[PDB]
Length: 284
Ligand SMILES: OC[C@H]1O[C@H](O[C@H]2O[C@H](CO)[C@@H](O)[C@H](O)[C@H]2O)[C@H](O)[C@@H](O)[C@@H]1O
Ligand SMILES: OC[C@H]1O[C@H](O[C@H]2O[C@H](CO)[C@@H](O)[C@H](O)[C@H]2O)[C@H](O)[C@@H](O)[C@@H]1O
Image 1 (cartoon, rainbow, N blue to C red):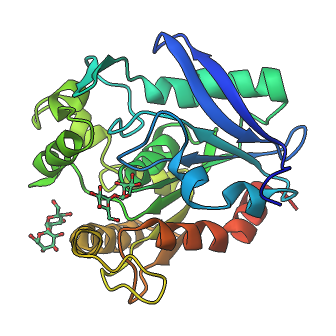
Image 2 (cartoon, rainbow, N blue to C red):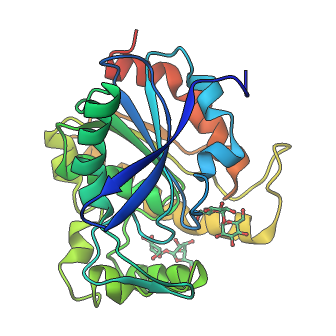
């Protein structure tokens, strides 16, 4: 049902960021595996975009999977930032890798008996690369990573400056505050194409989606959505080639001849990957 589901609106203290992170939550039951649904570049501070734009909770109720939707961190790339995250609205502390990989799972285990290990992270847009970086560096916790419509080589060429533009347009943040000048090693570290050997060695299950910029009847037929999806598509194709070349063998690659940078297409993927998540994480 949409109303009447056991959906919580948690307030999870983050020592590292000095505030309470709101977290929308639906348990799949005691000791259930978690699915972290990471929001896109323009993440709002009231509700995660996955809740706003999809019936995700509804789709995953009684799936044996806990659904975890952190709220906030627009333009954060769910990263630990070098300096305060200062945008149009003011400064906030961004230490999202710390939060997602310790404070949150520990709180969820202690307070809701959510299994802290063997989780998936699924992100769209900005959070698509973040999902893979979470699995790259925290494979115990994240054994599955979904990346929807993300720029997958952000440290390369125009990469850093395109990221700067977007953060600027979304809340007016500056990429220097996050991973520093493009010279800083933080860029390579958070580039999922660069971290492909990790993904392979950890045998991380991947779900990699990117549309082609052509809208079908689902909608999203507008130029920005079309131009954005097409623009990030090649990094998705190059990721695929590199991953296979590095001996990758645990990914689903989803590059249909349709799809724009719009929630209609992302929802469709989240819905599509439920049974795969259940098998890969042992929901049964
Ligand atoms: O980066 C994730 C955001 O994707 C959407 O916004 C992008 O694409 C829109 C077209 O669908 C553009 O209008 C917008 O300027 C882009 O940033 C989505 O609207 C947001 O909810 C996501 O956070
Ligand atoms: O940095 C983003 C991507 O840039 C290159 O490719 C882009 O540039 C052209 C458009 O201006 C097209 O080749 C394509 O649509 C874009 O993705 C680079 O080749 C990619 O690896 C980068 O992800």
